[PDB]
Image 1 (cartoon, rainbow, N blue to C red):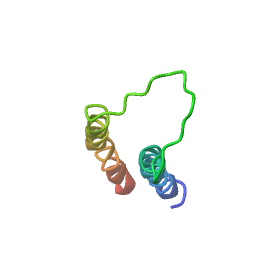
Image 2: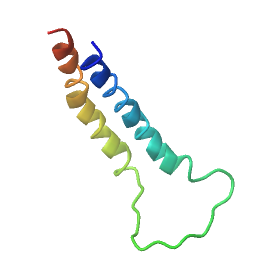
Image 3: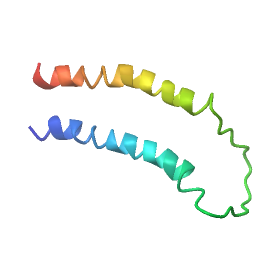
Image 4: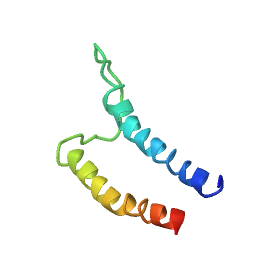
Length: 80
């Protein structure tokens, strides 16, 4: 019960790592600005918008609808 459930708990941890990946965004989003902004040199131009965030989230949540339904499938595959 530690191979699947802990792979699921690891997938939960990948989910936590998905939350931590989510928190990685906030690590990109929140951990980037605290009080003052610094000057850095970049080669590529970032996007960071509403149709790219809340949509990539709405696509993520849409991915959940699939993943959570896959986690519900996994929760379906958990017991059954």
